[PDB]
Image 1: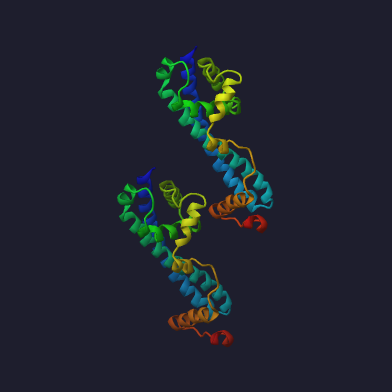
Image 2 (image 1 turned 135 degrees about the vertical axis):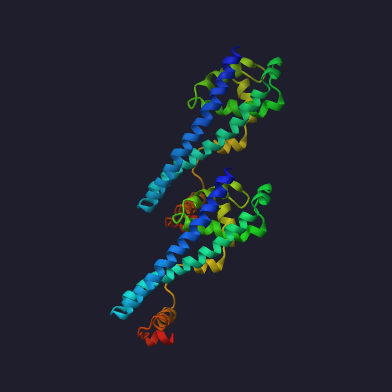
Length: 181
Length: 181
């Protein structure tokens, strides 16, 4: 298969990973001053949704870094496992997590479309329609938490609002039922 | 991280600390003659608000000197703790007080923005959003008093007015309920 198209794809993935990380950092700083505005100005719940979007983004940041490590370590053993024909256990975790998150990351990046195709084009043993679904069970559970879509515990969203109000110097009063939870 | 940008930042912090200390001293002398005017001229309560601003400033002066000692002692062990990766107990008090007062001092100085970022960039153990909030509990309580925003006891504001009237030779009569308090 097109393994150097795959490789330069990965390189662009890494480049855009860095770029998107940086851009989202920038706008996240602006948005944190903005959240200081919303919290300072009335609807802390509006700021609560804003910071929900932000903590979502931060889950994405952490997941981005984890998978950046994964694509880079897979890139290390390009020719080596390319000599092989099945995936090894040393890369089974990375491959499983990547295969699992790839559909979640299909939209975020178009290179990864080809990266996943070439992955599945690379293997059939524990690879394919369901065989890939069988081998993908070794996905990183930590990334899974960093890729879980949920409301954080309102004690923790309150703590994010508290540490924001700390860092950004607004008055925040958590809901004591949740501030105790 | 940018630890020499941090270092020259600290140097500018110290320079402006000295400069602002000197400037506020100068204008405070002028303002003390001015307070002698207001006390001499009618509204001692107007002078009372003026000297409230001044004693506030003096709390800032004392806090400035304390933290000047703190930044300089941290500067002593720049490379040493830089070799380390977590903060030591020998600097835990200074770091906690600095981290705690930094948001209060965010506005006073723009270098300290970076100084706090690099601080948090220096550590994660008892550092971060709430971990830094956890480790900051070792702040100087004396500085905390020198950084507490409160009305002094009116026996003491009366004593400041009395010792001003002493030094500046105006007639001051404290409110005997407070002059006894």
